[PDB]
Image: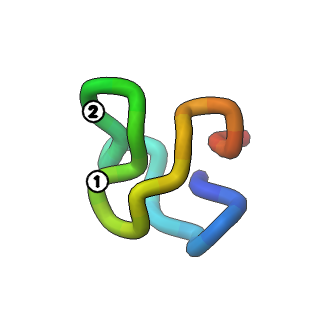
């Protein structure tokens, strides 16, 4: 998941969370 908004890991792409824009480091 994305720690900054809680979107599902499957929603990251190109090094960012494609929902809220967070960087890849914030995924857990």
Q: Nearer the viewer, residue 12 or 16?
A: 16
SS at circle 2: strand
**Which of these two is toward me, 22 or 27?**
22
Q: Are marks 1 and 2 in contact (CB under 8 Å)?
A: yes
Precedes in sequence: disc 1 or disc 2: 2
Tell me the number on the disc at residue 6. none
Q: Residue at x 40, y 49 (%)?
A: 17
Quarter of the picture containing the C terminus is: top right
Say few, some or many: other residues with alpha carbon within 10 Å of mark 1 (under 14 / 14 to 19 / 20 or more): some
Q: From the viewer's perspective, tell me whether residue 12 is left or right of residue 2.
A: left
| Residue holding disc 2 | 13
In the image, residue 22 above or below residue 26: below
Mark 1 lies on residue: 18
Image point 58% across, 69% down: which residue?
Answer: 6
Snapshot quadrant of residue 26: top right
| 10 displayed left or right of 1 | left
How far apart are the alpha carbons under marks 1 and 2? 6 Å
Side of 22 relative to 13 (left or right): right
- Percent coordinates x, y for residue 4 in the rendering: 66, 66
Figure label count: 2
In the displayed structure, 18 sits above or below 9; it is below
* Quadrant in the rendering for residue 13: top left
Where does the image place residue 19, in percent across and percent down from the top left? 32, 65
Q: Position of residue 11 (x, y in %)?
A: 31, 49
């Amino acid at each position: 998941y994305c720690s900054d908004c809680g979107a599902d890991a499957s929603q990251v792409r190109g090094g960012y969370c494609t929902n809220c824009g967070a960087s890849a480091d914030r995924i857990r």
